[PDB]
Amino acid sequence: GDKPIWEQIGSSFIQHYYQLFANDRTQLGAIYIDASCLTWEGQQFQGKAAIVEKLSSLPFQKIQHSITAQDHQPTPDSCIISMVVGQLKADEDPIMGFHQMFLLKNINDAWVCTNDMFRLALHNF
Amino acid sequence: KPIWEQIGSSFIQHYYQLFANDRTQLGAIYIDASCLTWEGQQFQGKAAIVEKLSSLPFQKIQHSITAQDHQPTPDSCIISMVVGQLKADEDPIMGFHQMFLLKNINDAWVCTNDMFRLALH
């Protein structure tokens, strides 16, 4: 009846994910199920624990994000797959591009992340 | 090499080899209920999707992957995400991002979800 549900749920996940990413990373566990999977700069991590942990150790202090584009589509298995392209500035590190992906699933009547992929857009020299 | 990587890599090679050579046959890696979001525009169904890709205003588009990540999901699917460069005819080289959600239907891996984005230098 207007803006697709997967586009409401998705942008709403993105929003909540990044905010939490900038205020208290040790709280990300709640948006992932136990059988989750994360890929950070080529590196894969399985299970909730190993994910939260990995994210808790990133050497950054202040981080900011600017969602430049975000695409959402429903999948055959009744899931929501999202693609994010944007930019971030980590402390006084130079502004850089990046892309992320999320696969949300409805569990306990709440949408939770099962798959997550992140990778900085490396400058070419 | 993890099995999910073998499937995904083999799929993107097949996908970009078709995309560079014969775009009109790109239907071979989609299903009728496939969905594509290109530069923000959505094309639902194999018919729409192929027609969109097939008619892009150019004779040849090359694609070079700068990096590719793959991953398996709880419900037997595979997510492939690429970041690389492409060049349409004589047009200048441009960055892009692309993600594919794969599933095995009819005993064959096919793409059900496809999102593409051009890089903003």
Image: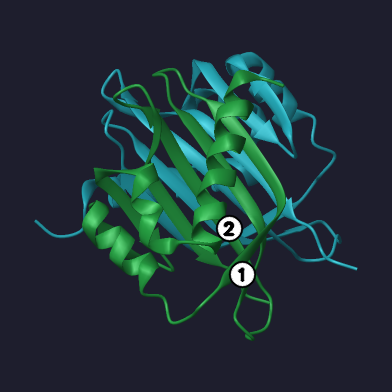
Chain colours: A cyan, B green
Q: Are marks 1 and 2 in contact (CB under 8 Å)?
A: yes
Q: Which mark is residue B44?
A: none
Per the image, label 1 sits on a secondary structure element best described as loop
* Residue drawn 44% across the image and 17% down it: B74
Badge 2 amino acid? His
Question: Which badge, 1 or 2, comes first in the chain's sequence?
Answer: 2
Q: Residues within 10 Å of mark 2 (few under 14, many from 20)?
A: many
Q: Position of residue B99 (x, y in %)?
A: 51, 48
Where does residue A113 sit, x and y in percent of width and height? Answer: 46, 30
Q: In the visual, does A65 lie left or right of A106?
A: right
Could you say which is closer to the camera, residue A95 or residue B89? B89
Return the residue nearer the eye: B74 or B62. Answer: B62
Tell me which residue sits at (55%, 29%) in the image: B7
Taking the image as shown, residue B97 lies to the left or right of residue B46, namely right
Q: Is residue B40 above or below residue B106?
A: below
In this orientation, which residue lies closer to the viewer: A55 or A121? A121
- The quadrant where residue B3 appears: top right
Kindly identify which residue carries mark 2. B97
Q: Is residue B85 above or below residue A5?
A: below
Q: Is residue A23 visible?
A: no
Determine the CA span between mark 1 and mark 2.
Answer: 7 Å
The numbered dot on residue B119 is 1
User: Amino acid type of disc 1?
Assistant: Ala
